[PDB]
Amino acid sequence: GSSGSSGDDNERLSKVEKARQLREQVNDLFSRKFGEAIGMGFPVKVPYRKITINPGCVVVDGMPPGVSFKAPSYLEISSMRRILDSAEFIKFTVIRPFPGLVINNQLVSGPSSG
């Protein structure tokens, strides 16, 4: 709990490491949860934008009080935490899929064997 700067070093990070990670947790969190809204057995991309401009397509519930849903890039550390605190509460309703969206199956990757 001391003032410092960011850089390549956990010792320096601290406040960043917390955010960096959180960002991942939140992101994945939504991605994962979202899957349910798509009955997907994996975390899918969460178009916060679309949901923003209009949830109609994909909705988001469980959100905490006095907290707005959005990408973890804008959300703050504390912000993320909350969401996480309600990770179990988080929810996503797919009223209507996007014009091109896809469900079921898996994307195309290529880590090694693929």
Image (tube, helix red, strand yellow):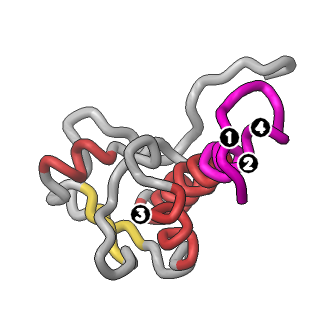
The Cα atoms of the two marked residues, 4 and 1, are separated by: 7 Å
Amino acid on which the number 4 mark rests in the picture: Arg
Expressed as whole percent of the image width and height from the top left, the position of residue 65 reads 33, 81
**3 or 1: tag closer to the N-terminus:** 1
Q: In the visual, does 13 lie left or right of 52?
A: right
Expressed as whole percent of the image width and height from the top left, the position of residue 84 reads 56, 69
Q: Residue at x 73, y 48 (%)?
A: 14
**Residue at disc 3, secondary structure:** helix
Crowding at mark 1 (Cα within 10 Å: few <14, some 14-19, many 20+): few
Q: Are marks 4 and 1 in contact (CB under 8 Å)?
A: yes
Q: Quadrant of the C terminus?
A: top right
The range drawn in magenta is: 1-20
Q: Quadrant of the N terminus?
A: bottom right
Expressed as whole percent of the image width and height from the top left, the position of residue 45 reads 46, 42
Q: Are marks 2 and 4 in contact (CB under 8 Å)?
A: yes
* Circle 3 or circle 4, nearest the eye: 4
Q: Which numbered dot is residue 14?
A: 2
Q: Are marks 3 and 4 in contact (CB under 8 Å)?
A: no
Crowding at mark 2 (Cα within 10 Å: few <14, some 14-19, many 20+): some
Q: Which numbered dot is residue 12?
A: 4
Above or below residue 65? Residue 20 is above
Q: In the depicted view, which residue is nearer to us: 2 or 79? A: 2
Q: Which numbered dot is residue 37?
A: 3
Q: Residue at x 68, y 40 (%)?
A: 4
**3 or 4: tag closer to the N-terminus:** 4
Amino acid on which the number 2 mark rests in the picture: Ser
Expressed as whole percent of the image width and height from the top left, the position of residue 33 reads 52, 63
Q: Residue furthest front?
A: 3
**2 or 1: tag closer to the N-terminus:** 1
Residue linked to disc 1: 4
